[PDB]
Image (tube, rainbow, N blue to C red; front, side, top):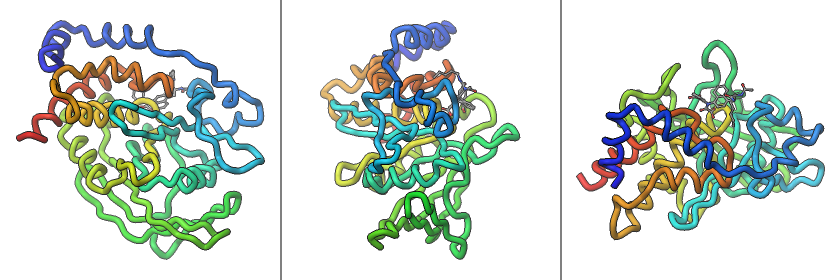
Length: 282
Ligand SMILES: CCCCCNC(=O)[C@H](Cc1ccc(N(C(=O)C(=O)O)c2ccccc2C(=O)O)c2ccccc12)NC(C)=O
């Protein structure tokens, strides 16, 4: 079970140790492309790179690099593109990826500024009348409308391929209340955010993978993907409590390094799942 496992681990101050076990067991693959000198300025952090085998390739012939990894969960039959918060010079690449991968939704789990520094570039327009044009990738982005709520904001955006004049609707799911330090006391708001994403169909098969990101695209992004996949898995199994979240994180890490960066995010993940399951069945 995972319910009791939480018990055993929690009332034993074992989280820190469990997390370390994962780190030690986690997969390790080459990130050659990410380390090429010409891509140095396409990476926010020198210690956070995508494995070559699962990296997303931009369809351009100049440089197909972008710091983004395709996490492909076979059993749960769900795919996610985890990426770093874009940089002032990679916003065009970012939206090019959304277009090419036919993504329907973009999930943001951080704020543009946190701790007095920029953790992500302002990659989307804040005003309907002030659209954005990414000349390098020939794309136009317009803010159609947004619904601001207590712990998160949902925006309707229009992305247009200026080259073909084709347009699409992208939904921006911005969790705006992640705490300055640690993790949310309760996963309730986080769960509602997730369900809201699910409801839109952004995580469904008839669309490309959702694009998920925070700053490095491994920590908060990891809790989101881990929670979703675990919840979905419990829906497909005869024995829901057989789902081993640690096993799921380890599988996920085969596609992108460092998913879930602290014992806290790991614990929060268990919480989100455990609670999410109860809510779904009442
Ligand atoms: C993959 C190995 C990670 C090695 C550690 N590296 C780091 O922490 C950082 C990159 C880096 C990685 C992960 C982060 N991070 C993330 O959730 C994330 O943006 O992925 C967090 C890590 C620990 C605790 C909290 C958070 C959080 O934001 O809630 C970061 C959050 C803010 C700023 C940077 C971050 N590297 C450098 C050079 O500063």
